């Protein structure tokens, strides 16, 4: 109906989920830079290059919060070389 939304959220497969969070992570990531340009990301892009450290590293984690439910690890933007990774760390956090 509609309320089933959630059910669908936690009802989607890992793939779709990853392919979903990824897309978000990508846009979100680039968003942290203060720009809506995904062309500046390919999932497997260098986060460090993207311009992530602490503020930009948190700004993303802050948004990613609405993409996972938690505050994500402060190292998330450290152990993750690219978004493709973030998708994982987040997935593992979702699983």
Image (spheres, rainbow, N blue to C red):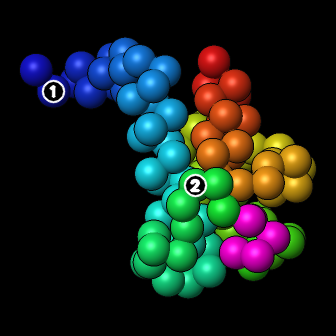
Asked if residue 46 can be seen in this view, the reply is yes
Q: Residues within 10 Å of mark 1 (few under 14, many from 20)?
A: few
Q: Residue at x 56, y 83 (%)?
A: 34
Which quadrant holds residue 78? Answer: bottom right
According to the picture, the residue beneath numbered tag 1 turns out to be: 2
Residue 8 picture location, percent across and down: 31, 21
Q: Is residue 49 magenta?
A: yes
Left-right relation of 13 to 95 = left
Residue 51 picture location, percent across and down: 75, 78
- 74 relative to 93, above or below: below
* Magenta segment boundaries in residue numbering: 46-50
Numbered tag placed on residue 43 in the rendering: 2
Q: Residue at x 69, y 68 (%)?
A: 59
Left-right relation of 7 to 4 = right
Q: Quadrant of the C terminus?
A: top right
Residue 71 picture location, percent across and down: 72, 46
Q: Residue at x 15, y 27 (%)?
A: 2
Q: Residues within 10 Å of mark 2 (few under 14, many from 20)?
A: many
**Which callout, 1 or 2, points at the residue further toward the start of the chain?**
1
Secondary structure of the residue carrying numbered label 1? loop
Q: Quadrant of the N terminus?
A: top left
Q: Total number of numbered labels?
A: 2
Asked if residue 70 can be seen in this view, the reply is no
Left-right relation of 77 to 67 = right
């Amino acid at each position: 109906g509609s309320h089933m939304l959630r059910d669908r959220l936690a009802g989607l497969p890992r793939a779709e989920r990853t392919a979903e969070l990824v897309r978000l992570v990508r846009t979100s990531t680039a968003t942290v830079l203060g720009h809506d340009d995904p062309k500046a990301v390919r999932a497997t892009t260098p986060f460090k290059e993207l311009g992530f450290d602490s503020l930009a590293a948190v700004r993303l984690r802050n948004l990613l919060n609405a993409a996972t439910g938690l505050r994500l690890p402060s190292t998330l933007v450290f152990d993750h070389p690219n978004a493709s990774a973030v998708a994982g760390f987040l997935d593992a956090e979702l699983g």
